[PDB]
Image 1 (cartoon, helix red, strand yellow):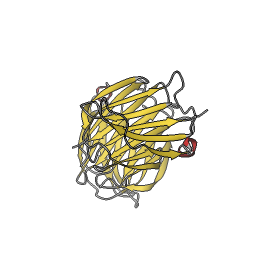
Image 2 (tube, rainbow over the protein chains, first blue to last red):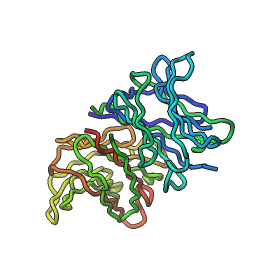
Image 3 (cartoon, helix red, strand yellow):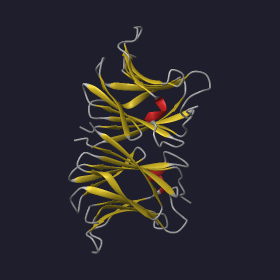
Image 4 (tube, rainbow over the protein chains, first blue to last red):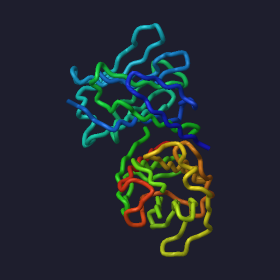
Length: 152
Length: 152
């Protein structure tokens, strides 16, 4: 039997999961706005490591994926160009879905897979965070995270 | 490689799925409104069989679950008491998740499992629908159905 957990994440905030996200599981971050005229979503481990850090950068015009340990510097950054071309026919909202596939995270923006991210740091996701720089986020102030767990 | 698909279904309509739902796949219906003070969500096979009919009846204060073959009577019905209580999580919104577990459909309202539904018709889901008794739906006029497929 599977589980659905729901979380409201304000920008700047972090949440601890009532059910960990492991191999086979799914996180979708739901935004009720799309402000494309910077912004980060994070899958963290119990010990505070960044298993997946996703940064939408409008200025540079790239989406960035990286990982790091706590108190440690960033690892090998992966970079997808052209932010707006990942939200094709999005409208005024967006969703960011992460599939935990064991060796990789699959990251899908709306209906389109944006990266098959080979994991740099492995393990269970026990926390999620969402932040932006100043009052400019490409997403709504509150992002709803939904987890689907106990799937495999 | 798994896949996310997003469908808008307005009250009274049916949508064919670009990717069929099968064993180990998920569908969630998102409603941006909740009017508890009638309303049906359906999963259908290629042949038009209702694999899962979920009907919310406020007057009778029950959630009804059933299946039926194309143009044939409703099979054995299953009922859960007290609609309002299955929704205690969110005001002004809700989700209804259906997990296809092979032999069972697990229905989850927000975070609360409401039924483990022993299938009365087997097979793959290839369309969804959403119905309401005119202008008095429990949900928003448009519901967003998100499928997570290619999971197994």
